[PDB]
Image 1: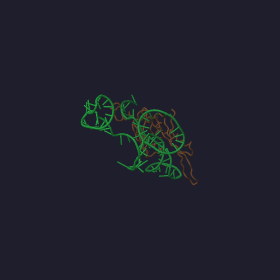
Image 2 (image 1 turned 90 degrees about the vertical axis):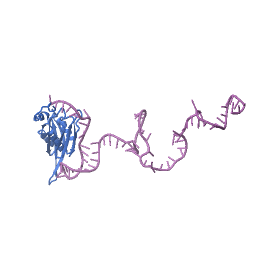
Image 3 (image 1 turned 120 degrees about the vertical axis):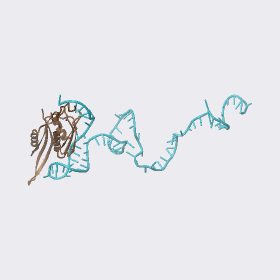
Image 4 (image 1 turned 45 degrees about the vertical axis):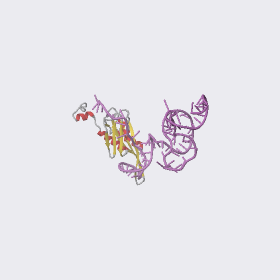
Length: 158
RNA sequence: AAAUAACGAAGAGUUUGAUCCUGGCUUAGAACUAACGCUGGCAGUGCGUCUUAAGCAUGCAAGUCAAACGGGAUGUAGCAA
């Protein structure tokens, strides 16, 4: 189903040697099924196209299931990676993905449709994506939490 | 799987040979009793000395009561009253 692929970053880096300085390309990439599966990948190469391909291949291995809810997330989460804090909050329908660059990329790849978000702290795009994925770790699902708390979905409110 | 509530929060450039973090500066927006530059058809509504509480030609902006009173003047009746 036409896996969405969004190129977050294509940075050009270098290391110096006795001869001079040698250049290289790093590509940070997010792929997603669009229906609950999403993953990210990092690639490095001597040229942009090979770096892009490597990042794609790496991303296709870190696919993980995130339980979406009718096109949004069950509850407000805060993802803290190293210094990138990302607050994500589900919203009433038809609001639209109110998110920055990397957050919007990962969200449309995931399939979410209607959230608000804010990127506090560092704006390093790669760290922001990783913080978003930590928030994905923090998100829950109703049946399991109810099965581990010894309740049932109706009883969980009464 | 679900229920209810929420009717609303977007980033980016820039320290380095390159990187992360800290950090300031700058930037896309909405405004004003605005001014200036180029250009300029109309209508409706609203607004129009933010500075010298500086000096001011001119005209107007607080008068009315004759059924409160004694008189003057005028016209008529009146010889005069």
